[PDB]
Amino acid sequence: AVPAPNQQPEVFCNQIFINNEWHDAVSRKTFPTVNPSTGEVICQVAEGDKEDVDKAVKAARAAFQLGSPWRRMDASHRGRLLNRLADLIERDRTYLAALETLDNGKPYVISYLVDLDMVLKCLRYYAGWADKYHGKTIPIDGDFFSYTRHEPVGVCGQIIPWNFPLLMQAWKLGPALATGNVVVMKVAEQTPLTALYVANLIKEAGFPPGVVNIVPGFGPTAGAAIASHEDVDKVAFTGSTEIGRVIQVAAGSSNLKRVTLELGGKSPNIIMSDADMDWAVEQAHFALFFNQGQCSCAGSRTFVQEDIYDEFVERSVARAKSRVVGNPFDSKTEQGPQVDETQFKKILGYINTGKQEGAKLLCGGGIAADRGYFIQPTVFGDVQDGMTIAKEEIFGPVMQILKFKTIEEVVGRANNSTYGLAAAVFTKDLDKANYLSQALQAGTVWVNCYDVFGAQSPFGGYKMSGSGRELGEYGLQAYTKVKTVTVKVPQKNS
Amino acid sequence: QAVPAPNQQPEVFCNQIFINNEWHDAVSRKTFPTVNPSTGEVICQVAEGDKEDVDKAVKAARAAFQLGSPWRRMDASHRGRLLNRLADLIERDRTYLAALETLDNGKPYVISYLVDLDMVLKCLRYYAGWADKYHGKTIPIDGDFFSYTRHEPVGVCGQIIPWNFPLLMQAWKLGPALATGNVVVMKVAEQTPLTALYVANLIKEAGFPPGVVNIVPGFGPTAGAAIASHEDVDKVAFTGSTEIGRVIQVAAGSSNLKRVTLELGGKSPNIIMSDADMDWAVEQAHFALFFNQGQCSCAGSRTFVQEDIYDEFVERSVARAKSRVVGNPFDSKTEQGPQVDETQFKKILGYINTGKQEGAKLLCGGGIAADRGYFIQPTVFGDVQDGMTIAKEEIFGPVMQILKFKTIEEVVGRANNSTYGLAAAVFTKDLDKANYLSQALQAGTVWVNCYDVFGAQSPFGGYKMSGSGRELGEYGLQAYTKVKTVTVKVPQKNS
Amino acid sequence: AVPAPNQQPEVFCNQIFINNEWHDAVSRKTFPTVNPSTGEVICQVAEGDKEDVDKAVKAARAAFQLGSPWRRMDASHRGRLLNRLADLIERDRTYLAALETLDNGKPYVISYLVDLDMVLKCLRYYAGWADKYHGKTIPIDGDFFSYTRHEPVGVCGQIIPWNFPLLMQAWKLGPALATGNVVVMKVAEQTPLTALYVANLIKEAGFPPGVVNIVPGFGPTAGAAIASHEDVDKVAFTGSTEIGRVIQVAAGSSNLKRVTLELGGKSPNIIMSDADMDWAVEQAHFALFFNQGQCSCAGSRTFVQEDIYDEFVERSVARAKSRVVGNPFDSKTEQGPQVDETQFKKILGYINTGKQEGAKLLCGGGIAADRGYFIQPTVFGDVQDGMTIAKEEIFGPVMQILKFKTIEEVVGRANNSTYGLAAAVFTKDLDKANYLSQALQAGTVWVNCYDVFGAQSPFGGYKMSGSGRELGEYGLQAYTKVKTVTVKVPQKNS
Amino acid sequence: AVPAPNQQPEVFCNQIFINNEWHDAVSRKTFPTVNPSTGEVICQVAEGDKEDVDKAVKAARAAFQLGSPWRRMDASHRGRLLNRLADLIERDRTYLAALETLDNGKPYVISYLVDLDMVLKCLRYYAGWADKYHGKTIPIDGDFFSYTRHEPVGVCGQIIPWNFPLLMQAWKLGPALATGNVVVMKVAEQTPLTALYVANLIKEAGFPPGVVNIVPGFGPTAGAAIASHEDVDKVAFTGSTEIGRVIQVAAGSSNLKRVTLELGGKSPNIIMSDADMDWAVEQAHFALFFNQGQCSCAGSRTFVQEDIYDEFVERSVARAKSRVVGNPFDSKTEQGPQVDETQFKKILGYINTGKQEGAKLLCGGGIAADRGYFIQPTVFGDVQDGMTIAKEEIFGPVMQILKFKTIEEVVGRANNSTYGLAAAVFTKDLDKANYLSQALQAGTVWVNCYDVFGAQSPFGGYKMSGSGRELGEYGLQAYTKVKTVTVKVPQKNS
Ligand SMILES: O=C(NCc1ccc2c(c1)OCO2)c1c(Cl)cccc1Cl
Ligand SMILES: O=C(NCc1ccc2c(c1)OCO2)c1c(Cl)cccc1Cl
Ligand SMILES: O=C(NCc1ccc2c(c1)OCO2)c1c(Cl)cccc1Cl
Ligand code: NA
Ligand code: NA
Ligand code: NA
Ligand code: NA
């Protein structure tokens, strides 16, 4: 049950957010953001640059000063505030789902039922962590009392992508604020709007000024400013593998700030011959096509055992051909447009590359509409490991199906990747499942499911898919600094 | 490693009461005989501790626990060193202790050596590593305060251990209590005090301060009951029959509100799905029931077998029980030794006669295996029904119950229809069946495609009437730890 | 600020709460509850007994059945429910605060600012714990995958005292529900009203029927029925130590149910000569007299170093004499009546006992008013360790001041007690504080403060003051069962 | 209680350690290691370069392969091996302490009682962690079973310094091997000998070949090759802040490997007017001069309250003048030589800068012997914040004493540093101790003591002092990779 969408949501916030106030760029420059369904400009947005980031970092640093409201505040109260934000986001849930859909392209039903639900669950989960992340009292040798405090890292720079604007914002803000940090956040030029509105609610919820600061703008400018800043303590970045290198380089050439990265992937989805066919087919479709295919953990390498290959493919093509593409605000729409023109063209490039290399086109393969960046759900069969489409992140509605024989074989082929973000195993066999989840070199391994995310369970990549983890108790460690205090005592006893 | 040839008649060097690192006679000067179950002959006399010797033990322990004492001041890391030393000393005397364990208890020497001793060693060494790693917390309390917790020793811990695993039970008790800075007054089984008393000697040699560990051999209703009722015992831990754990607890509740943990009986279900690996399932089910002469609280004493494989399984099961070699525990061919004593001997025989009378199908064995010693034939009952006494009551002997079932919903309900809940097992190749069953079974430990798999790392304990609280793992430390909160006014609290 | 109270609040809930339903006793019996300030009957309340307990237990068992809504419910959602309950409670904060004062006698200002706030903070704390109490994956020897599940204990009997009716309810429900248990709760016959109103809010919050059942009645009847019930998996009791020994006895001869107890105390409050005099004096007054002296952790043995003893006693007597006793609804009132005639009489007896013992009566010592159960703030000086008033829990506004010379001396004297619930030290010296915080045999040691409770920090007794802990992560341990699952795997790797 | 030293220990191991075998450098080149007490060459050592690092890494990768002896080994057994290694090191304790002194210069008595003891305690501490670092079972939403495996990070590059050759090696090997990692370790060109002997003991203990590989050589060559390697999964560096940057840059332009740094410091040692004079003076001397002043956490900024400043400075100078410099093998020697000519000249240069900037040279300040790199214990008084010697890590026997007035003042000046490795407070006051321990921006705060290390308490810096922690349970985090496994189940229940 979903409330009727306002298909033309008004935009209220489009400037830079610092100290709970709205600011034009120092330069007074602005940039257009576009509706990827129509190609029409939604509105102009403040274009943040190095000098704007400087203002934002200075505001955060002051907010973080010892004895400030934010620093003195009860941990439990940081929790109440996160809970209040959740309630405000829920109050304006219909509006935000619509705004997300307008700015990003994903179906309003998914924005509402998935993205918005997950945002509420993430903030609410982390609200609970604010006063429960304990330090230790330590049985150290000698006549001493030793213990640790789990202190905030400090000023945290956070750069989030366009594929899940609201959710990614929440994945970052939850652990950061629960642990008492202050934030300087750069949002994607493609999808700045929803985050800017949330900043208004952050103000409304009662967060002290300077605790959260959002600077819309371009990456080569605003993003690198954060990563290179001499007073930023930590930088978390979710984006492509390409941009990620550009960040850790800039971040290491400054003040030795802490760095975490959530990057691309080429995740294998393995279908053993004893898997439930109907289930494995629907899940493989879901695994790849979700969010217009725009997921780092997309199941973009579908390994199918030879004995069931033909039937699996047969059933998969029918499912991809029945996938409804169109107006994101139509309840019946399964697939919206790609986020922008640059993505649109790049996806079409990979499709054409697939054909040249001898992959077998089974459906789609071309443009799905003359208006907006709609691409047809595309499926490639008989893919081989050495193909570009088998190796590179496409980030589009393009599915690759490979055939294997043995379980030992597929382990080697699934693991032969510079990526290692996620993987899946579909089988009914207890031993096969335990064998594969242990042997697969990925941060998350799903068994008989896919894209199962909980605020409670960590997500992150092995290898070149990134470092560190988000979500769960683990997501706190990156936003925490350990101080050991060791006190001479008259006589230590047990 | 290879099993060294055993001295089949090892000498006894310790048979008295151990208090403050010294050997005592009982006050009454009374001693009692401990028997060799393989021959029925007396091994030696053992000082017979009673309440008055327990009072000496508790006084001793209390003194060693005093603020400023060597034990209380000792670095936690050092308590770990002490535990490793003890382990090193036991490994030195492993051949001797393994043989002594066989002499006093009856279990095959090869098993004492390769199983019991290895597990004792692994248990002590594991907890040696916990000594300096069980942290309290610092806590982000509201207001201008600094709040933290100290995990302090619970104090004077009375520990009563059974006879089925004398060395191992000792280790399971000493490991966590010593790692966390406690002192102990231990009462060992009258059937098997010898090995525990020799280890008391090793505890001295290892360097533990006097009074940290005190051992009082004696009888249950006297020595054991005195620990449970003592006004200066802070914790009592009892492993044994469900029947006696009831008594022990009843005593603790009427004394000083001491902390109590129990490790009691069971009638654990071993569930064989039709898709199980047959040969594997057959050998594991045999092991699951017959191990240690069937003398395990977690014995797989209700063998549920899916109807399609029932006949084959029962046939293979009876073949294996028929081939199981019973005899002298020092002969390497022996898989089964005598039961622990005559009382058990007869109780098991009684249960067998009950099973026959109540209409269970006697498939093999069924009576005495030798004229001398407490040897019983490995016994298998087929067509066992839930309502039968032998399907309900713990037998603690080499008596196997095999029950037929049809569906997975059926077996879960039947397995869970028990006052016990110590352990359970599931043999199947299907992921969903394993997961469905491991979640649904009301048992403290669930084994999947294996049985009797223990590790110092993984907690062990029962649901329902099989006791309360756990042993082993990090959880074993909780029952031996006391939490103190210290909350301090500070000038200005900041994150 | 504090809103004006309705001094004659209406009563809505006075029956037995089972399956979200209000029931009369099977016997149709009711009992009168009395207003301690006036000695007048407030209303009649259903008198539950063994048959009513038996119905409650059955309902709880049924709600706890595998596949039930409460068992299948996401842990995070149990969290939502506790937060909703807290919200409904805060909604009715002004009303519940007045009802608490009417039935119990404590000053309304304190019911509102202390009791009700701590109730809210408690439930909101545990809401956070619902989906964060993880089991473990364990590196066991051999080719095995071993892990633990932290399952609920099941049907939990909870018996709560009359001194903090609402807060003790929360201390019990928070952890039990966060961990997925079901509850059969016996409330005190002196103060059943506020707890019954909360049950109404538990139904309104959306808790499934049977998850919380509340049976008002008497101890020898309803209480013993819970403790002795064959189908109750755990019993938690807070109250006098004598009655605690009975509850622990009932559980032993039934079904080996897990029992935790929170019992009495005779907590030492240690004042070193280097302490802040003004703070120490006001804190020692607070520590003994708070809640009409009706706290098990009351600082009922005030040890004062001999060099500041004369001055401390002077200030302490003056403070006691100025303490305003009267209508708990008058904002000027610091001290209401004792909870009932039985307590009233007990306190009078203890006062006389001290007098006959040769303790010096420095002020008070009699009845403070005609109506209700009011007792004059009373102070004894030159108290000795062997005195009955120095050893037994008085649970009234009766202060015991003792003189000591050295720190090594006061440690011994402080510890020479069969109780061990709490302790405090007042000093400015770092080493003195550490020495004493380590040496005192108490579950809680306060330094330069007293009665500082936080939802995050555990509370419970050493020795005969009880077993187990409430509050904090520790509060969850008693409400969880550990299950180990150990699985054979093909080949264990790190 | 110290065994007599062999003042000329024989060298048995001087090559590259790969696969438990001793290797010459590919180029066959070698370099001299010097005795800093005599300036004379002890012996030549294999000069490993990029090609050799390449061999070692391949060796490590092979030992880490799924199904290998190290990967299949019981975790408890990894612990048994660490204990065996510790026992072997204890067997050869006299020899190792003598060789440490010979190569490094530290007093033999210190090498024996401090260094080797701490080495033993570190290896034994972590041996105990081997089978106790659990993953989690997670109460995720939905019908799933979700859990984490704590897997090894893989091939770990470890570059260690020359100030604590043996202890540093153990600080790295302990956590790394306890978690099942494999290691390529680069030892200091100045002190490579003891570490290579320890590798012979690693072979003796029974560690599978390729689990530990040691490549002696130079920083710009061997050290850089490790950091830039495309098959190294993690890099841990300890040394100057300068080189730490080089490492973090090289380690970012390669394969996004994990990086932890332990860098320099300029740690504030704060003496309040109510401190114990005798104790504070001896401890401030220890804090600075320990190990020829060669400790990153040295108390190289001694702040003294003006009321006690004069007396503290007088006592400190007297103690510095009394410090015995000489042959490290002489039981009376308190201070040996600096590590090498480079450091020798660098410290004398800092001394020169100190005099040129107008800090009061109170004692020492020159060369202490005609042979070897001995420098007199030096004390500067009236040091100001803006002086080079008050800002830069000197890493030698050069003490700075500063005057302050208020606790608010000293807090601001102590934190006014790009370094935050450690700090200390000497006071008898409870409140002052707590205010400072919280306010000081350092990774370790000592109260009424200094340089108190325990295997159990974590160590590491804030800001430019590095990232991450060593020792304790936290020391395990940088060596662990988290895999989340999420499994579809029939019907989830609590
Ligand atoms: O709808 C779901 N995932 C969609 C999804 C895919 C990729 C994502 C994501 C959500 O969040 C970030 O990346 C989903 C499902 Cl089927 C089961 C459990 C929990 C969740 Cl959240
Ligand atoms: O008001 C307080 N305590 C009063 C109090 C006394 C005894 C109690 C209690 C509260 O809760 C149960 O027992 C109080 C104080 Cl002075 C400081 C910090 C936090 C709190 Cl909650
Ligand atoms: O000798 C000690 N520190 C000397 C020391 C200084 C700097 C260090 C170190 C040891 O290890 C690495 O850095 C020391 C002390 Cl006084 C007390 C407790 C534990 C320790 Cl280990
Ligand atoms: Na857009
Ligand atoms: Na015997
Ligand atoms: Na009342
Ligand atoms: Na050298």
Image (tube, coloured by chain):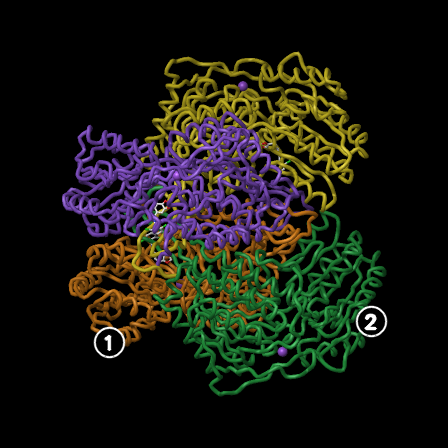
Chain colours: A yellow, B green, C orange, D purple
Comparing labels 2 and 1, the label whose residue is closer to the camera = 2
Image quadrant where one finds the N terminus of chain D: bottom left
Estimate the x, y position of residue C351 in percent, counting from the top left: 27, 73
Amino acid type shown at disc 1: Lys
Estimate the x, y position of residue B61 in percent, counting from the top left: 43, 72
Q: Is residue C2 visible?
A: no
**In this orientation, which residue lies closer to the viewer: A103 or B149?**
B149
**In this orientation, which residue lies closer to the viewer: B88 or D348?**
D348
Amino acid type shown at disc 2: Cys
Q: Residues within 10 Å of mark 1 (few under 14, many from 20)?
A: some
User: Dot 1: what SS?
Assistant: helix
**In this orientation, which residue lies closer to the viewer: C346 or A225?**
A225
**Label 2 sits on residue:** B364
User: Which residue is pictured at 19% across the width and 28% down the height?
Assistant: D356
Residue A396 lies in quadrant: top right
Estimate the x, y position of residue B34 in percent, counting from the top left: 61, 81
Residue C163 lies in quadrant: bottom left
**Label 1 sits on residue:** C355
